Image (spheres, helix red, strand yellow):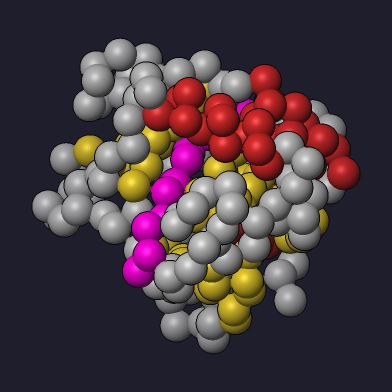
Amino acid sequence: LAAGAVILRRFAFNAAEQLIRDINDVASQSPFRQMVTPGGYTMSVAMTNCGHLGWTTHRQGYLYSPIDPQTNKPWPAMPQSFHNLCQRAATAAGYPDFQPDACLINRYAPGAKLSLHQDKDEPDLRAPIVSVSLGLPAIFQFGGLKRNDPLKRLLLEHGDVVVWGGESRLFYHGIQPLKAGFHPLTIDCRYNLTFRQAG
Ligand SMILES: O=C(O)CCC(=O)C(=O)O
Ligand SMILES: [Fe+2]
């Protein structure tokens, strides 16, 4: 299916309520904003970050910055619930030495999407990315190392954690338009946390 990927469905179910309270706390310092891609187009996914470094869009491309380009202040600290859940997920996946210094928080409104891309801004591509899904379900689509590779679909639901390691770490991926619906903890959206080793 996906070489190197360890899928832990509903792993973050118990931590969900606290993770959502902490997303709101992070958002009060560094608000969710729809980032502008280097070409001048606003993304449909709303983003923010927590930790020492944060994923951002810039004029010359994409980069990690210790400063929030909107607030001009540092990104909020990595919440304890975030650190604990990532550590437990990474350890269960065979990565006990994984220490993330960045967590990109994505918010998906109904219809929000993320087109095919590779995560290649990190210094060591051998280091995995821990993905945590919360709220409304979304269809995650992935291919291979090159753009013309056949697409495979995977539904990511509330509490689903995937540790993208090995070959899966380099796969082209995205999110199909979020279907409208209801979730008791997020109301009308989906949140996705992606823990990265960026320094
Ligand atoms: O929403 C997701 O599950 C994927 C997010 C993603 O690929 C990213 O922000 O780089
Ligand atoms: Fe990505």
Is residue 37 visible in this depiction of the protein?
A: yes
- What residue is rendered at 52% in x and 63% in y? 182
- Residue 79 position (above or below residue 169): above
Q: Is residue 87 left or right of residue 83?
A: right
- The residue sitting at 31% across, 23% down in the picture is 68
Q: Which residues are magenta?
A: 100-111
Is residue 153 positioned above or below 185 on the image? below
Q: Which of these two is toward me, 141 or 107?
A: 107
Q: Nearer the viewer, residue 187 or 71?
A: 187
Is 139 on the left-hand or right-hand side of 162?
A: left
Decide whether residue 84 is among the magenta residues: no
Q: Look at 26% across and 55% down and name the residue there.
A: 43
- Give residue 193's quadrant in the image: top right
The x and y percentages for residue 112 are 35, 63
In the rendered image of this protein, does residue 127 appear above or below residue 23?
below
Within the image, what quadrant is residue 60 found in?
Answer: top left
The single residue placed furthest to the top in the displayed view is 73
**Residue at 32% in and 30% down:** 31
The answer to whether any part of residue 172 appears in the image is no
The answer to whether 167 appears left or right of 20 in the picture is right
Number of dots carrying numbers:
0
Q: Would you identify the image quadrant in which residue 48 lies?
A: top left
Quarter holding the N terminus is: bottom right
Q: Where does the image place residue 46, in percent across and percent down from the top left?
A: 34, 47
Where is residue 44 drawn, in percent x and y?
Answer: 29, 58
Residue sticking out furthest to the bottom: 150
